[PDB]
Image 1 (spheres, helix red, strand yellow):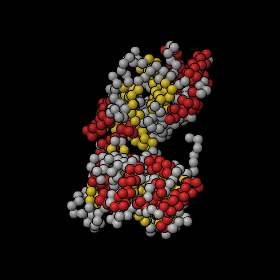
Image 2 (cartoon, helix red, strand yellow):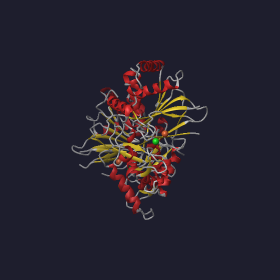
Image 3 (tube, chains in turn orange, cyan):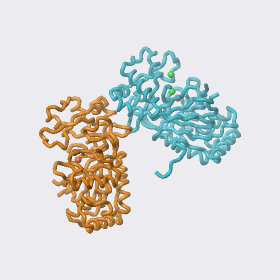
Image 4 (tube, helix red, strand yellow):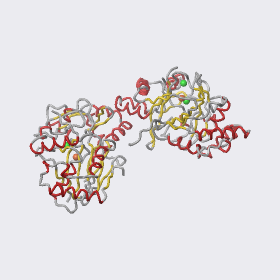
Amino acid sequence: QPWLHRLDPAEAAEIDDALDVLLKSGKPNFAASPADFPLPTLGPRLRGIVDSIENEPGFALVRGVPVGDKSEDEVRRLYWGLGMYIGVPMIQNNNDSSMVDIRDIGFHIDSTDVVTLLCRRAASQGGTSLVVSAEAVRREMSWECPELLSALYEPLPFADVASPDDERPDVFLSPVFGRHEGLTTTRFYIRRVLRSQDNPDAPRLTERQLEAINKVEEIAARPGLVTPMQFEPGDLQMINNHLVLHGRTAGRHLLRMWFSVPSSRSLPPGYEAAWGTREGGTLRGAGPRWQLQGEFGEFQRRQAEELGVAIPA
Amino acid sequence: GSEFMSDQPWLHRLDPAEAAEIDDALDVLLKSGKPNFAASPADFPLPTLGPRLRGIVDSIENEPGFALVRGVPVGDKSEDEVRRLYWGLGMYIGVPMIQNNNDSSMVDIRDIGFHIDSTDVVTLLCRRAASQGGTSLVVSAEAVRREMSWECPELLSALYEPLPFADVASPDDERPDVFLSPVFGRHEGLTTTRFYIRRVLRSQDNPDAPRLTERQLEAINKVEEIAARPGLVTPMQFEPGDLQMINNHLVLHGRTAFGRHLLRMWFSVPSSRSLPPGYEAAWGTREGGTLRGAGPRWQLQGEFGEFQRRQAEELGVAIPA
Ligand SMILES: [Cl-]
Ligand SMILES: [Cl-]
Ligand SMILES: [Cl-]
Ligand SMILES: [Fe+2]
Ligand SMILES: [Fe+2]
């Protein structure tokens, strides 16, 4: 498939050699640069793949990352090395983590420009990853139930993933479907919309809005629109959250990273509350207060200058 | 990519050898002594351009849904000779259709209103171009529908429900026959459109046709408004020898205001799309790749009808029984 990019032996061996440089450098992750994880041929190719998910269908699966003979610690450093050719990593939670373990789901986006998942160990049976184009869903609705689209273009309340108190979350407004200068952007997450109601000041969800978001979920789950993906050790999935909704079917171990990327799209008016800034190619996304602190923060600035990602002041 | 050509991808130029091939083909046709309705590709041989023409007509089933062939040698020909040349080219395009109540299968166009023609593929051969203006305009119907899905989705339902159209095949234009058809439809993943405001408004002259509701009038007006926007329109300035080919299921066409002379033909084609339920009234048959379109009663009669059957068998166009 066009979204599948396989690594050949030389490229896999190139990653092993890159990790050796990183391990032998005596530098910790947050002090490293791409020169400490050299990918002479795979580097430019990875940048190109990340650039390509700015277009439909908005995701890519890289296959063949050599993780089988590595320790868990070594895989994380390898993953960190690959991330230096993807984007600027972001803190993802209130625990100052920039790499989250997924071990032992309705369609949704992650609150970041690009999310990646590296599979170290695959699920025995279930755990099939599901991805769908948000624009394809919007287009089905435009044929089948256009009367509901207006509800998804008006801003709806979302609980902020960065809320310190999840029982009384901070809330921002965002449309589910938007577009700016011809580039579409989506935000969909039923749980976050329902949780927004725990803030008594947030607007109340009308039944029309509830009907519309439920319609989005129903259509996204249809066979004709879904692309299933059964992760194998060494798979690196990359998703553009402006274009893709992702989900999962019912000793797995995946590693998640969040990235700001230099090719991200500028956003429509009013999207500052949800994303921090409208301008594309900037350091943005969930939990602004988490970012740009300590050694990790100094890595973000160096990495942003390396890839050409602007840091809003 | 790595190359960026001057010509648009929908522009197909003829080289000298291809032009000479048409000149030679016309010589064969004129020297055979056969009239148009008795001829076959054997009487207008295009060894290299024939297959290329078939491929271009097949390719307009996909986006962008139109093509402009440039360089047909018409400059030194009489009006009569250009018509014979055009007829020869049509034997590699599709099965020609009767277009009006005077049994014409080649109509003269002489001296906005986006619309389709009531046929699968319409072609225009430019013998003479207008000195100033007269720019041909084409727009993607699905692109118009998609703007509406963003800007005014509440109006789309009115365009998916059948609307009344005056039938071009009506004997009495002041008392037209009327059929119902949606403005936008899709079947098995392939979209189809019908749009022509004048025809929709003229349907009201038939007292039996349904009266146009406010939502329908607002919706069709919105389609016209969006189609005329600069960002969606593709202009084309015809030159002598240009052959424009348009797939009416995907493209709406129009013209800007002003010795113009174009020749129009209508074709059933073997790669045409199957249509949604209820489209029989407007098209005759839903099945794709069949002889269909406006005025079924006009077709398959006399010598022209026998040419249609021979031509349909050559190209693989089915004739429903
Ligand atoms: Cl999230
Ligand atoms: Cl017509
Ligand atoms: Cl009319
Ligand atoms: Fe997620
Ligand atoms: Fe026309």
